[PDB]
């Protein structure tokens, strides 16, 4: 299992409704859940990234 | 130009062109803040020279802080290096040189000046390599600090593809030597880069206080005179109004360092326009208009007007 | 909206929070310097129009320099394209109309306008 | 105090002092904007303490 | 170490933000190495308590 | 029968035994407010009855 | 005023009158726990006014 | 300090800042009731320990 996050539901629905409302299971806040190196630096056009991380560049100690 | 904001999306790689566009935006925010109190583009914080090497005729700077009209700040104490020494030998037989400070323009196709190999276009941003690192515990590795590209241009400085801001003015003395002239100062973001002004305005204020003291000695000593209807006593009452209303503002402003001089102009203009209608027969046109872009032939004739009215 | 600000030392993974929060803090500094003897429900520097389409029911804007009271700068010669054509097909009385230059309000969990998805509230957006 | 704003053109390895000296220089520019008209240093905007904790002596702060 | 949200719709993660090492000292001590600004004044009251003068004023950027 | 202060998160599941264990805490608070000067199991205010059916074996309460 | 009390079960669902009456009920208990604060009626603990606005024939409150 | 009782009507999102403030106001009411009589920094009610471990210098609390 992976602790996923958002998918933002398109009506917020936690307006406390006067004319018609329902409870039994679906209650929440505004964001749900869904349970179900040696790399270089700032050079040009296309190969900066190690994808999302950027390390392997300032261990000058140990 | 066209300044662009970057978007720091996740998965957007890295480019060196992003950081330059970011850092040329907060400077634009500084102008958008600062232009809520400015008529006309800017000038000199401080400028100090070394006139000792004048019999071997040269000129070099010591300490120079000047803001430029695009929002560029120059600091020799913290950020930039001193401009190189000037050679006056080609204007060895003339009288006046008006020396401006120069940075080249920036166009949207080039950049820095690569070793002067292609020097038909004067270009700024000379690099350097100084190693300073020690805000966590070590100093070792080496970064590329940026320095500007400053010169001095004196006699055909009007051939400028450059930005100019005048700093000093040389005249031939009777022994053929150039010396710095104590005269009018190209424009100011302070009242500290002109010791001639700080010598004149203290005399102005100390001259103002004594005439007020003389007036108070005339009337406070006699209790009938505090509410009399003499035709000179009404004028003297209204005159003490005009002086007492305008002393403590100026005494606050002139016990002070750096503060932009338009504010001082708005306080001297009230005193002049008040006292102008008291003992004269001359036109309202004696009040000079304010020219900041000039080197200020406004501020000495204003004080020459005020020193005549107080006697 | 808290404004965090990071520390850098000895190799840290570059994350976009470390740049966004730094940009926000330098916006906040310039506004706090800008208060200092002013009022700040601030307004408009320059607004210029295009007025030929008024025999039709349309309207178009050519230059907008607006500073919003939270301190966000909008400078239509530099890094913002002009808003689309206003619509005049649903107007009954002709003294009614008062035009306001809108701008979507930012929240602390949202982001940009990804097209291909629908919402009852818009945001600033990746364009180009 | 030897503030060094750096440049980025190409091939520059990333290194923290660029970011640190950039962030300091922005503070210094925004300070020099404010020091033009006012000639005043900084001061206090708001300082609110807690009074119900005084006779049981402690001192807690709320907004500084 | 906190969890700052990305402002483009994704999940958050754990970064290292900076926090100043502020402290509260008293004027009658030694205060060489610090950089100070006075904030309040305490006096002693009749039952032997502490209370605040309404008469001090700090240096103020605002009224 | 213990009483639990419920925790109001955000982005969780609501269940009615947050509302009930919220509501049953304030009554227990007012009990311990009341038991600080007074010391008995309390009683009746203003009982009133009906008497018409009393020829037959019938009662009817009216206000308690 | 017929202060009702709501019922939270596994099928009960959310209304504003669910919360308004539960708000009013614990206000109403605060009188029922007073056996001396009902003897004398409800009171006044602080009321401070300004006098400088009186030559202008205005009046303004400070603390109530 | 400030205490912000929420407005209840047919618009609001179900935000967690309502319930904490509404529950915080009831403690202030139940304490202003208790300050109609007595005047006190509050005291203990029960405090009983266990003298078994005390030859090994460890102290525990059974009920507080």
Image (cartoon, coloured by chain):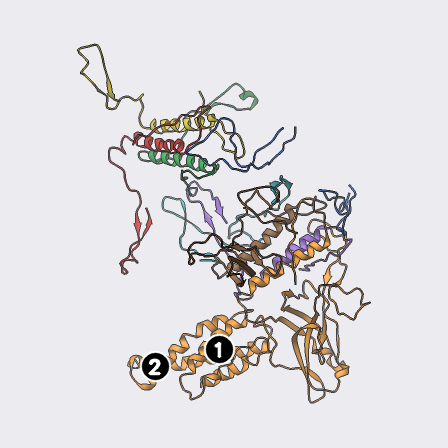
Chain colours: A blue, B orange, C brown, D purple, E cyan, F yellow, G red, H green
Q: Is residue B112 visible?
A: yes
Is H10 located above or below residue B80 in the figure? above
Q: Which of the two discs, 1 and 2, sits closer to the camera?
A: 1
How far apart are the two marked residues, 1 and 2, measured between alpha carbons? 22 Å
Are the residues tagged 1 and 2 within 8 Å (C-beta)? no
Q: Nearer the viewer, residue B273 or B106?
A: B106
Look at the image and tell me in which quarter the N terminus of chain B lies.
Answer: bottom right
Whether labels 1 and 2 belong to a single chain: the reply is yes
Q: Is residue E32 visible?
A: no
Outermost residue on the top side: it is: F57
User: In x, y percent, where is residue C47?
Assistant: 53, 62
- Which residue, given by chain and number where applicable, does mark 1 sit on? B205
User: In x, y percent, where is residue B106?
Assistant: 70, 66
- Left or right, B216 with respect to A56, comes to left
- Which residue, given by chain and number where applicable, does mark 2 sit on? B219
Answer with the quarter of the image where residue B271 lies: bottom left
Chain letter for the residue marked with disc 2 in the picture: B
Q: Nearer the viewer, residue C108 or F37?
A: C108
- Left or right, B20 with respect to G12, comes to right
| Residue at 71% across, 42% down | A52
Answer with the quarter of the image where residue B105 lies: bottom right
User: In x, y percent, where is residue B148?
Assistant: 72, 65
| Residue at 30% across, 58% down | G53
Chain letter for the residue marked with disc 1 in the picture: B
Q: Secondary structure at mark 2?
A: helix
User: In x, y percent, where is residue B113?
Assistant: 77, 65
In the rendering, which numbered label is found on residue C57?
Answer: none
Q: Nearer the viewer, residue A61 or B28?
A: B28
Q: Secondary structure at mark 1?
A: helix
């Amino acid at each position: 299992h992976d602790r996923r996050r958002i998918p933002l539901k398109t009506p917020l629905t936690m307006r406390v409704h006067h004319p018609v409302s329902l409870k039994s299971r679906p209650v929440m806040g505004d964001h749900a859940t869904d349970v179900n190196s040696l790399l270089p630096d700032a050079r040009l056009s296309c190969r900066p990234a190690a994808g999302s991380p950027q390390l392997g560049r300032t261990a000058v100690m140990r | 130009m066209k300044i662009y904001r970057p978007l720091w999306e996740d998965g957007a790689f890295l480019m060196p062109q992003q950081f330059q566009q970011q850092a040329a935006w907060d400077v634009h925010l500084a102008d958008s803040v600062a232009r809520m109190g400015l008529a006309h583009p800017w000038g000199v914080v401080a400028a100090e020279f070394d006139d000792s090497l004048l019999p071997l005729s040269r000129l070099n700077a010591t300490r120079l802080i000047v803001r430029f009209p695009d929002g560029t700040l120059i600091d020799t104490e913290r950020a930039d290096n001193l401009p190189p020494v000037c050679d006056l030998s080609t204007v060895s037989d003339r009288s006046l040189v008006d020396i401006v400070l120069a940075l080249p323009l920036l166009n949207a196709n080039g950049g820095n000046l690569d070793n002067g190999s292609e020097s038909e276009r004067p270009r700024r941003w000379k690099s350097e390599r100084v190693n300073v690192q020690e805000l966590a515990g070590h100093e070792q590795s080496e970064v590329a600090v940026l320095r500007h590209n400053l010169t001095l241009r004196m006699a055909h400085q009007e051939n400028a593809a450059w930005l100019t801001c005048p700093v000093t003015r040389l005249v031939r003395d009777a022994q053929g030597q150039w010396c710095r002239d104590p005269r009018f100062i190209p424009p100011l973001l302070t009242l500290s880069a002109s010791p001639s002004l700080m010598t004149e305005l203290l005399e102005l204020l100390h001259h103002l206080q004594a005439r007020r003291q003389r007036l108070m000695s005339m009337r406070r000593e006699n209790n009938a005179r505090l509410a009399d209807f003499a035709v000179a006593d009404v004028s003297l009452f209204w005159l003490l109004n005009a002086l007492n209303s305008a002393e403590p503002v100026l005494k606050e402003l002139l016990d002070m360092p750096y503060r932009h001089p338009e504010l001082l102009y708005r306080e001297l203009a009230r005193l002049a326009g008040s006292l102008l209608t008291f003992s004269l027969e001359h036109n309202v046109d004696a009040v000079p208009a304010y020219h900041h872009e000039t080197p200020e032939n406004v501020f000495p004739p204003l004080l020459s007007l005020l020193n005549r009215l107080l006697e």
